[PDB]
Image (tube, coloured by chain):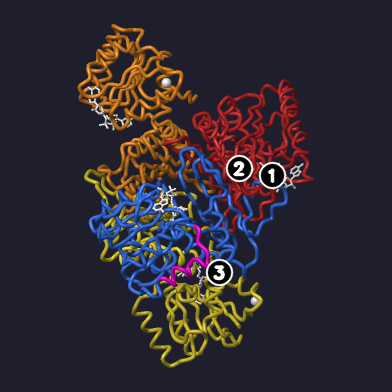
Chain colours: A blue, B yellow, C orange, D red
């Protein structure tokens, strides 16, 4: 269909600009960034809008698109429970337009997390290794900390990871994130990588997600665009569309 | 429950004897091997049997178990549609008896197959690498062939793997199973290993199962023993006991 | 040193221009591409040239550089015995000029092949897996085939890889390159990757090289540039600069 | 050769006894453990000894062996610069006798450490990840610590590993061993595994060693046994025998 992009020259936005044109099914209509009026959406006959902007502006963006007709695929972060009620509330009176908000539009990332969550229950041990370029400020990554927290929740009815360590050097066993060891590698030549390691007597199971650039998000978002016409109202996360949960 | 083991002295059977013994909720009631009469099962008031014997004997074992109303958890392989049908005929006469037959009792293997199936529609490319000890007679393994067939079925209606190969040495691109390349490594020091690879521009996802030892089969078997009576009649596979939906 | 680039607008050549400019022991003194007079090098008082052009232009360039006493670091491919002998012939007249020609300037790639060669004899089994983006025409890659032949040469007089394969689908066991299986994965989202697997009972050894960028060729070329005057005549390969003995 | 095992009831020693028995070219001549007199070696006309005993007994063992012109392949650890010099001094009396002492007899481990040292010079980043079964007492492993130290030494005169980390949880970045991150994974289902990661913008290089059981040391020990008399006196490490 006919696609618009908000935050159209930002890191993710500029990437989504090139991707829509490169698609056969999809035609570019509106590319709005900072300082731009939202009229250019109605003036471009847009069917579907992608939003990768900023927490401080996104709420104003949505109030518009709903009161209009254009579907909204939102990647922009900073969301609370009271914030979704506002989106749902605008959609109560307007039951024809569909909206989706996702904290992660990378399909492989969403699949990894889901598999980790399903697998957690069945193994004695779980650890996370994440590996990034050496310009990363935060250790571990947001994704690894979140994965660890989720696996730990999936494991709340099981004993802790077995570990006879009785002598160690500080830091050897990783960050302890809700009882899950998370290790963080920072290596020139790498980009963004995460392995989830499960183990039990006689077998191991490993899940690896590798992102080599900011196009890891593209198929996820384009999936959510090609498919936003299907389900009405608000949908949170990419997982419903992946026939997962 | 009172549990007997058929094939009690075998490689897997001896493992199961030990686990049934060590399991506090299960009472080991019989250990039968070659030349032991099946009457030993009933003398022990066996309620459930684990069978890890040989395709040549399992049908006669199963006939006795079913006739006597003893639940059966069968790891023994060689089961065909005809054998499954025969099992179901026998169970008609014993509506309260349950039989669970699984071709793969490693939970990590079953999970990894499930995950491959769930991921398969959401990437451009999919291949399987399997790696085994150099005494393996079949290439690719049953499991890899099964995995590639599942992945292909999952991807029905979607474009084939992209591949510009125009010059190749015979065999480089692996075995073709329904359009899914399967590569088989035979290496001293390995046991049984399989990696499923998924990719699209900007990201890859990998699921690696490593099978090191036969103790890996224990949780799968014991889960089936504990849950056996939940489904009267024949259940094929471990998947349903894993509650993945 | 005063360094020029032949093929400065090219995929690898522009990467090299940037490299020379950024390094502050080297002065970028010439950036020639198609249609540029070679006189530009002399009018730049160029001491060393990095050549990443085309097999069709390189000997001509080389003849110029050698006649003009300009040291040459050549990445351009298509070099045969006859071409090396011609270069040898030109350097007889110019004994204080050095030419280094390498088919692979990626230090990581060079090292991995050297390691594979050193390891090959001490293991019962050796296999090569290579994985590339799906726009690659040739399977296996030149590097993989070449790595498999080095491994085979090193393993002369040892038993073949053990392999009890009695039933297989064609292609499952990979391409046989001098007795060494080579498996070629073609997966969207990959670039250039190679894994060499060694195994004997009780241990395995894996060497994995991942090539993400053309900047992978940068350190090899710059090392060659910094060390080219240290060896008269013709050096073939990057290996001799890495001081691997 | 007639080969005796000192420490024949031990984890590794018993593995060596089996290996020497199954080896077509070698004749098992003695099996000694604690409380067996060393004269059983001379009684069996032992020509070479494999020693996987204990740091407290090994020098006495060596003294006896050198005195009796019996070659020694020694895996027992605890050797010091001082202990090497003692063995070398004893060897002046018996220029006829060869001793080989190695901290690691798994050829694949010795190869990976060699590869790591070589590669360490050529990349911006180096890290070590090791992965063991969850009954392991020490983190990181002896091998992983040894490796990180050798990688550090190779990288003297290079800038440190780049790393912009400005916010971390404690432990996320591993143990710092001489400037080399070392991460210790402890996981049920695993045995003993180590990965060495090197990288520079553009490319990475990884070397992975996986030990599957105690038989990982066998070929290295047997090779040492076979080649021991090539080099008179004391050889430290297996590396020389791998004709690198
Ligand atoms: N869900 C996911 O998979 C992902 C979500 N994100 C999130 O997306 C958001 C944006 O992504 P980045 O490219 O990292 O940020 P960015 O700072 O690079 O891009 C933001 C862009 O939005 C524009 N913008 C600001 N106010 C606007 C307004 N009222 N109307 C239209 N455009 C406006 C800016 O000019 C800028 O070009 C961030 O909050 C980030 O956390 C980022 C990556 C993935
Ligand atoms: N489904 C799964 O996850 C797995 C299935 N298997 C299968 O299980 C079976 C057994 O495997 P292994 O333990 O490796 O073989 P095994 O040959 O070592 O064990 C079989 C045992 O059954 C005994 N046996 C033969 N006839 C008998 C009879 N009439 N009554 C009682 N015992 C009898 C044998 O003497 C032997 O002790 C094979 O078919 C194998 O393929 C093995 C591993 C996993
Ligand atoms: N040894 C190594 O590690 C590597 C070698 N190569 C080889 O290097 C060569 C170039 O590689 P790419 O950059 O991919 O090719 P490219 O086609 O992208 O660039 C070649 C450049 O050379 C220019 N050129 C043609 N004739 C010229 C002349 N007479 N004087 C100056 N410039 C001229 C072209 O206009 C073009 O800009 C190829 O032969 C390729 O196989 C590529 C990668 C690595
Ligand atoms: N270089 C290498 O690759 C390896 C070296 N080692 C080292 O080798 C030594 C033995 O290792 P493990 O088998 O794990 O220990 P272990 O404790 O299982 O074996 C030591 C054996 O030596 C015996 N012993 C003690 N005094 C003796 C004597 N005077 N004569 C003959 N036997 C005697 C003990 O009873 C025991 O059977 C240790 O120093 C260990 O650190 C262990 C593994 C690998
Ligand atoms: Mg019990
Ligand atoms: Mg410069
Ligand atoms: Mg023998």
Please name whichever residue, D244 or C235, is drawn nearer the observer in this view of the structure.
C235
Please name whichever residue, C210 or D18, is drawn nearer the observer in this view of the structure.
C210
Q: Is mark 1 within 8 Å of ligand 4?
A: no
Circle number at residue D182: 2
Residue C97 percent coordinates (x, y)? 34, 11
Vertical comparison of A36 with A99: above or below: above
Read off the residue under disc 1.
A169
Range drawn in magenta: A78-90
- Mark 1 or 3, closer to the camera: 1
**Is residue D21 toward the left or the right of residue A115 in the image?**
right
Residue D16 percent coordinates (x, y)? 62, 45
Q: Secondary structure at mark 2?
A: strand
Quote the CA–CA distance across marks 2 and 3. Answer: 34 Å
Please name whichever residue, D122 or D240, is drawn nearer the observer in this view of the structure.
D122
Read off the residue under disc 3.
B218
Q: Quadrant of ligand 3?
A: top left
Q: Secondary structure at mark 1?
A: loop
Quote the CA–CA distance across marks 1 and 3. Answer: 35 Å
**A87 is within the stretch colored magenta:** yes
Dot 2: within a 10 Å radius of its alpha carbon, few (fewer than 14), some, or many (20 or more) residues?
Answer: many
Vertical comparison of B213 with C110: above or below: below
């Amino acid at each position: 269909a006919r696609v618009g992009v908000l935050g159209a020259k930002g890191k993710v936005g500029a990437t989504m600009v090139r991707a829509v044109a490169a698609a056969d099914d999809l035609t570019l209509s509106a590319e709005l960034d900072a300082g731009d009026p939202l009229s250019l959406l109605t003036d471009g006959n847009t069917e579907v809008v992608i939003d990768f902007t900023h927490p401080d502006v996104v709420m104003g963006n949505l109030e518009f698109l709903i009161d209009n007709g254009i579907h909204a695929v939102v990647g922009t972060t900073g969301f609370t429970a009271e914030r979704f009620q506002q989106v749902e509330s605008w959609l109560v009176a307007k039951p024809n337009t569909s909206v989706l908000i996702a904290p992660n539009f990378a399909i492989g990332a969403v699949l990894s997390m889901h598999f980790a969550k399903q697998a957690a229950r069945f193994f004695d041990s779980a650890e996370v290794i994440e590996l990034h370029h050496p310009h990363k400020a935060d250790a571990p990554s947001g994704t690894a900390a979140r994965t660890a927290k989720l696996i730990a929740e999936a494991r709340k009815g099981l004993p802790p990871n077995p570990d006879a360590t009785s002598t160690s050097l500080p830091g050897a066993r990783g960050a302890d994130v809700d009882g899950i060891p998370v290790h963080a590698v920072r290596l020139a030549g790498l980009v963004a990588h995460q392995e989830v390691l499960f183990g039990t007597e006689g077998e191991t199971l490993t899940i690896r997600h590798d992102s080599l650039d900011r196009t890891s998000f593209v198929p996820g978002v384009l999936l959510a665009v090609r498919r936003i016409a299907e389900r009405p109202g608000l949908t949170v996360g990419l997982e419903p569309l992946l026939d997962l949960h």
